Length: 592
DNA sequence: AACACGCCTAGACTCCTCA
DNA sequence: GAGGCGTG
DNA sequence: TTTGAGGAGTCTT
Ligand SMILES: [Ca+2]
Ligand SMILES: [Ca+2]
Ligand SMILES: [Cl-]
Image (cartoon, rainbow, N blue to C red; front, side, top):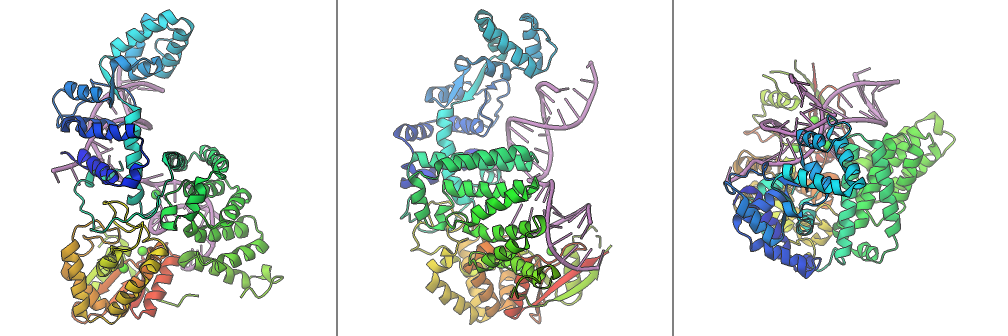
């Protein structure tokens, strides 16, 4: 089986064995999946090749697949019988036949049918052919017959069966996505990936019925379209699309299904239509801000912050952003102070957005403009250091240069991993708690790299006594214990796809063992507590470098900065917090 | 010099059709 | 979201 | 005529 079919069969098996997910398919749709498994390998191979391509008519001219068969005529015929794949005889709409033809093929057609401009562009010829065929039905039937003859043998994928596989992938996709935005990396690799072993346990339903899923899926397409508009810098298209989404979401706000969604725990409530429209409303405030409609942007941010149902984790980003627009763009210092107060009060705002609001506070208590207002009332200081480059040493990064400085300054051993180094160690020390039994709805299918609550407050609370026991054990751990825990997870789990664990991060198991030994129990314990407590807001801002001396076991955690980049809020909080745990932290600056 | 802010980024590549 | 570049 | 920017396709055993 080649990579594309391997990946497809994994996706299918994973979703079908899920009884509760299969409630969202009528018995005919389940029949189409049964029909696919009754196909030959070559039938399956070819269908997947066409499934991955644009939903459009394809000339058998253009269909080459050496690894399937030399001629695909019997393979197409199997898929035709099964009802997966139309042929010439089904191609009847004139618009569709004209699209399928080449510019020279339409030119010679336009000569025979005496069009006004036979040397015109394809679309003009197509629009012209459609006008003629409409006006004079008799001619239209000749155009259709003439076009189909030039078109030759061609084939299209049936939208009915396609839609069943689209929905299977949509259900499969939910659990692969840890962050917000078949996909390429999975299409290629998914067949070969071995996943952590855990116990699937589904107490709760995500979608009420088939109609609920279709409305989710539609909002997903709308979210996808809005992002693509913003990506291509078509900010007017995006505004209307976001306005359509706001209308479509407004129409739906009464529907009974939404009341079941409100009752889902946050780690499942992400997989609900209302969450997707809320995320579209986050994209809307982004578009309004780019079009300099800051009054309009602030209404939507106030609207979003007025509820706690959908995207609580985004509230930190919303408050910080509301404070900015009221302060710098609208110049309303009285709302700014209220916004910041309500912001800093809210226990959903964390780390960078917490600090950023507090930094905007100390900028107003020490500002002549806000003397007419009341009193209006931190981070620890860190050793900054400077070195020099030309960058070359031949061509090197800012981090590679700093590593050589720490190598010359005695630290023979070093890793430039940013957040992956502590994330992997966190994954390696707490694997068995990460994938532990007895939390319902967190393991729903066989291809998860994480429990669905990992990036939620639920993760720590749901595992509170087990984590506290391990966190304390790690704090009081001799190097023999740390080396043994890392070794246990390594030898049992090496290669297993876990979101937290980059297996290639450490050059060997020995390097992982050597590093935890230098870091020590108290440091590792505190890092693991933070990442377990609130991965969503503590994942980012860990320092670029760990450097350590292989004899002394002196180590520095270093955030490398080039000429023009300051500490982010999340970086300076991590430096302070690693200093409190009693590790030497440094900002290694670089200059020309 | 520093700092706060807006803005853009989005995989890497082949091949071939047609403005 | 995070990072890189340009602006005042 | 002559051509190259953009879109569809492809990627891992
Ligand atoms: Ca690090
Ligand atoms: Ca850096
Ligand atoms: Cl991006």
